[PDB]
Image: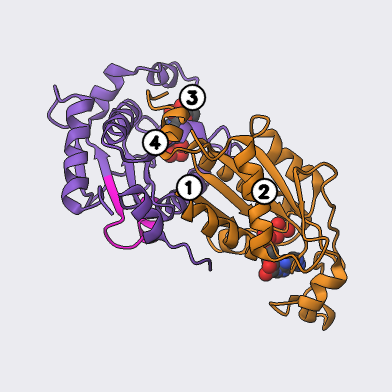
Chain colours: A orange, B purple
Amino acid sequence: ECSVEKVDRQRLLDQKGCVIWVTGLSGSGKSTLACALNQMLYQKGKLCYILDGDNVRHGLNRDLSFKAEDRAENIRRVGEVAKLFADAGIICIASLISPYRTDRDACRSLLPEGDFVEVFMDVPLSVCEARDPKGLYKLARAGKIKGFTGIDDPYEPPLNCEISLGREGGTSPIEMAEKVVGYLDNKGYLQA
Amino acid sequence: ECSVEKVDRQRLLDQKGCVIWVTGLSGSGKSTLACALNQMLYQKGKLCYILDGDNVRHGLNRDLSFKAEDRAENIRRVGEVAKLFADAGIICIASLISPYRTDRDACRSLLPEGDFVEVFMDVPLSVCEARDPKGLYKLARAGKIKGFTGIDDPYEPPLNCEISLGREGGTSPIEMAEKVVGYLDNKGYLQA
Ligand SMILES: Nc1ncnc2c1ncn2[C@@H]1O[C@H](COP(=O)(O)OS(=O)(=O)O)[C@@H](O)[C@H]1O
Ligand SMILES: Nc1ncnc2c1ncn2[C@@H]1O[C@H](COP(=O)(O)OS(=O)(=O)O)[C@@H](O)[C@H]1O
């Protein structure tokens, strides 16, 4: 143990470290929400870092597939990394499909109460598939991708998340980010 | 890709993200060097974070043993995590025995040239064993620990590290940290 503590890092950054865990089907707007939130927090002088499922999967998790056991390990490792970022005082935004409740719950358990903010992109499959920005649903339908979440692999929504976004429609990435920032501000995470 | 870039995070923190990779036998002073450096950088208003072999091994790497293949994975994952910290703009201090050259070299390869500073605690086994602060060498001699680095498992020193510390003796953790801080300062890593 070193003399420099988490509260020292928070004092330096004037914010509190935490994990914003963004979960949802492909196409539910996780990544655009993460980017909008990051931009908004940056402009307020707060330091964020995004752990994106796809990106981490080309580095730390390059060894993992999409078999259920590998998704569990993917989520577990991201959870541990996010905890480290939080301990460093960073507002860490994890954005992964993260389809299994038990695995997201395990990530929550790694952190002190209040430090893990589960954010659900509450968007139905039909809307996600109509967007299909990356053509993944198209690929899954054409049979190229087996066991695609929402098609032939399960997504289990959060039963008690802190924030639920996107259900209404005609709500923008920026408006949704504003809701998250408002929540963080009220919970006291935006000042030491 | 989000609009907020690494240079934006560096601008916010007034420093450059990097990996300070501290390697050496058990008892060579890695952890006291890491703590002294962290304290010193904190007092200068710079944000550091220490990834310590033992600690990470109770979380992210809780699944790994000390078999050579598991040490390789331990090092590989820490290298990827340290890269993320560097990308976040943090001065990331990795402090692991990290005994194999090929594995440390692989971590170096993950980063742009200049962003990985390999620091060797150049302290002979005999001095490390005389210190034996945690009683590990005692345990290895008594046979409790098989394949202990330096005893019955190999340590391969860096052939071309940026900084080599501790060989003289009567050099303190703080004096050694000062040398590292001087190097970082001169390389420009302590300002945006
Ligand atoms: N079978 C699949 N299901 C979902 N995503 C997949 C699949 N195969 C490849 N991918 C890709 O992997 C990305 C999702 O990765 P993650 O967010 O990390 O998933 S997770 O389920 O393990 O949390 C998708 O954007 C997509 O690009
Ligand atoms: N066989 C071993 N060799 C070295 N360290 C061990 C061994 N077994 C347990 N340990 C513990 O693990 C710590 C070292 O872990 P690491 O720094 O992560 O090692 S590394 O070789 O894989 O990089 C030691 O401080 C010690 O507490």
Q: CA distance from mark 3 to mark 1?
A: 46 Å
Residue drawn at x 51%, y 48% is B73
Which is nearer the N-term, disc 4 or disc 2?
4
Q: Given contact means CB atoms under 8 Å apart, are the residues at marks 4 and 2 in contact? A: no
Q: Are marks 3 and 4 in contact (CB under 8 Å)?
A: no
Please tell me whether residue B7 belongs to the stretch shown in magenta: no
Q: Chain of mark 2?
A: A
Query: Between residues A22 and B184, which one lies in front from this camera angle?
Result: A22
| Residue neighbourhood size for the residue with mark 3, other residues' Cα within 10 Å, grouped as few (<14), some (14–19), many (≥20) | some
Kind of residue sitting beneath label 2: Trp
* Disc 4: host chain: A
Q: CB of residue at label 3: within 8 Å of ligand 2? A: yes
Magenta range is: B101-118
Ligand 1 sits in quadrant: bottom right
Which numbered dot is residue A21? 2
Q: Are marks 4 and 2 on the same chain?
A: yes
Closer mark to the observer between disc 4 and disc 2: 4
Left or right: residue B109 versus residue B69 is left
